[PDB]
Image (cartoon, rainbow, N blue to C red; front, side, top):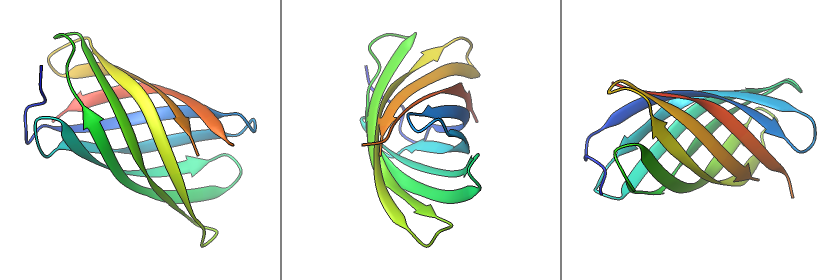
Length: 120
């Protein structure tokens, strides 16, 4: 199955990086086509480092319960640094309004992030 183009979802996730830092990221994923989506988000890392994240990827629905996705983008850090990031995750629908979000991502720095995705 496909995405519904125009679907807007606000998400909030907590990510645990391999360097023993922790991110909290709030943002949105907007499906622009049946399989592509844009991703924007503002994140905070517990090493005192805010970043603006912009990117996107591919996503489809295996079932009404599972929606895998792969994504890549860039994190515009508050150290005036720009770093590339990619992710691989899925959304597990738990209500018509809500979904559980899990994502494995890499930046030689890897992270696991869990959170929720609210469909607006």
